[PDB]
Image: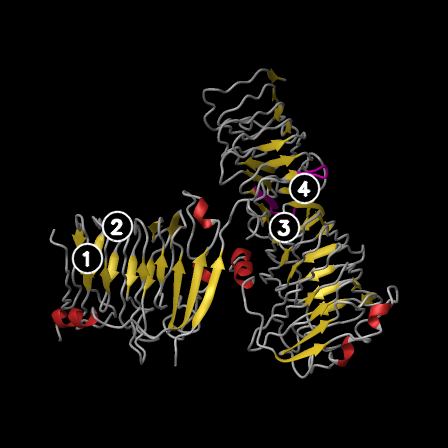
Amino acid sequence: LLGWGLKQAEEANKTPDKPDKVWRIQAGKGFNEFPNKEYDLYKSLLSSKIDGGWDWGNAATHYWIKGGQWNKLEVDMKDAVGTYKLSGLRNFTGGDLDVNMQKATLRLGQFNGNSFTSYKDSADRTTRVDFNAKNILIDNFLEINNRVGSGAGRKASSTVLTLQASEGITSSKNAEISLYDGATLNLASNSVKLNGNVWMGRLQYVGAYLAPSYSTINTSKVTGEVNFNHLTVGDHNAAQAGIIASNK
Amino acid sequence: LLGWGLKQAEEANKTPDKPDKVWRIQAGKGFNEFPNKEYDLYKSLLSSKIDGGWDWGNAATHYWIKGGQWNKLEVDMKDAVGTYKLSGLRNFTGGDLDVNMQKATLRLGQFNGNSFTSYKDSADRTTRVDFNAKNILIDNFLEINNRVGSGAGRKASSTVLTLQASEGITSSKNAEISLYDGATLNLASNSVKLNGNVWMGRLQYVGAYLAPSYSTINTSKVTGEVNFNHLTVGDHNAAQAGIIASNKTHIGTLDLWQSAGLNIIAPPEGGYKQKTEVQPTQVIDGPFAGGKDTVVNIDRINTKADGTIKVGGFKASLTTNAAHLNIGKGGVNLSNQASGRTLLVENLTGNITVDGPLRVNNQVGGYALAGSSANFEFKAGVDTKNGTATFNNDISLGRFVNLKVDAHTANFKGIDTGNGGFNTLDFSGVTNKVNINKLITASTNVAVKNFNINELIVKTNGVSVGEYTHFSEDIGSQSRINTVRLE
């Protein structure tokens, strides 16, 4: 009932969290010497400090960082040349990644899509999931602030999916970006061209036909040519989405 | 499920522990004046501050340091000349020994072997058991990270057995080194020669047929001649062991499992080298390239294969990113169950030179039934793509055995697949040439991109029609066959 103009203006100015256990992973040698290798990046680097899980209540998978979602991590490559896929991170609760991948083409999809959620606990935390790749090339679906299963388990709090590549964030025809009730996302490359389903706002729960369900795609400093193809605001609710674009 | 390449790269960079009660023992006088005495070293020095025990649950013996395993000790001799045996330390839980024995020959065996375990408590501690002897001369068995008895009592956490002598770590014929699910061990002398059973990975529990069971023998700075004799990776599990050697690794008998792995990794070229709480920089490497003179002379490969029957193969591997992979005269063996067993002889950034005959079920031709399609596999110079798979020996395929090579210029000398037929003689990843000198095919699935097979044999297959030598890809421009012979 608040309105998006209040909500984004008060959520774009926060402190991130209080993360204890700042795990600091760094890619060493071997990664930075094959320009065409097509690494995986979940199992080949991340999956030591990202654990699976089962929730008592609507579980299929459950991912956080390490011993509770109130922990950070980081990944400081800055030289690991290749092409890195994610391929299958579903119901990721986590917190405060920043996969700092200089000189690395990204991909977020092969044989499975992705998800980036948090939990509505007593902290009501964000996720602040950054990336710093070279392209991005999303190339499969992505479910920012989705539901765990259906109804059971817990509630989901907000999130941020910043994505700050440096060549152009293209996408695919079958890449349905489905950001929900709380999710925003920045972008800061030049010449985004999302050639797939941008789905701002959805029924996060199946019965909640009366959610406000805000969002934002704050493509804030995109210095080239913003270009959507298929924007689908709202689904069975008054989804008051917003976009703060960059004057084209 | 993590993989060894993550596990060792995150376990080689830790803090040891938080030990209270740093007992500091020091050998005084009397020890340093008999060069030939043959001391015992458990009872004569250690056994004041190492106590026995009984566990309620699967106990025979139980050793720790003093009042709980969270205590260190040390032994600072640095002059105690003699020859010191251990002889009988079984189920040692302990923690953080470093028996600093300068100018002292060691021994770890007489009338009884040894063990070095920890416990999987709420701390999940290592053991970090160092030594600093002059030779080592293991000379009996050793059970690093073993089980207490069987099942009962408690679980076991990780361990480290560093062994940093200064003359050469030999061993005995009856010295079975049995490192298990968690155990690693460094070595840093020159010219190791383990002339006994190296057993990486074992059933730590009797029912746990599904453990990952990693290990490592990081013979990291061994400045002389690494030399195994009998390496036996895996036992009824997918034991993904690894070795980070020092660019000359002669080994002898390799006895893998169906589904156990191996990662013999060469050095790099230059050689090696409330409140928010900040973990240290957990540096982790990726799969890198060997140096130039990185030699891996695995001169006999065997592969046992027994158990139940799965829908497919199991594909034991040995990722070997040295800039060579010579395989000598025993060549390649395999053993085949009802499903086709599979061997994965990779090389990331080197060559392959197999001068030995391929066998399966230990015969040169190696016939196999239609369901048991044995799958040999070679990947020479994968991530450089100028890697050759030279087979300087006459290979021989029986029936339902499968070769595939993904190399740059896979040279050969002689191929025998027409004796049995039904042999998937794949060449799907060959960059340019397959310079086979002699070819025998009857009912074969040869597919070469470019070649010059300067002699051809075209055999029949009795009465079966439709089954023949079926070239199934591009033969291309520079191709050549200097002699075709239809029998």
Please give left or right for residue B54 compared with residue A124 in the image.
right
Q: Residues within 10 Å of mark 4 (few under 14, many from 20)?
A: some
The kind of residue tagged 4 is Asn
Please give left or right for residue B56 compared with residue B454 in the image.
right
A194 in relation to B66, above or below: above
Q: Residues within 10 Å of mark 1 (few under 14, many from 20)?
A: many
Query: Which chain does the residue under circle 2 lie in?
Result: A
Name the quadrant containing residue B425. Answer: top right
Magenta includes B474? no
Q: Which residues are magenta?
A: B327-346
Q: Is residue B129 visible?
A: yes
Work out whether mark 1 precedes mark 2 in sequence or the reverse, and give the earlier one: 2
**Residue drawn at (26%, 49%) of the image:** A171
B352 in relation to B439, above or below: below
The kind of residue tagged 3 is Ala
User: What whole-number distance in Å separates the C-alpha atoms at marks 2 and 3?
Assistant: 43 Å
The residue wearing badge 3 is B245
The residue wearing badge 1 is A219
The residue wearing badge 2 is A169
Q: Secondary structure at mark 4?
A: strand
Q: Are marks 3 and 4 in contact (CB under 8 Å)?
A: no
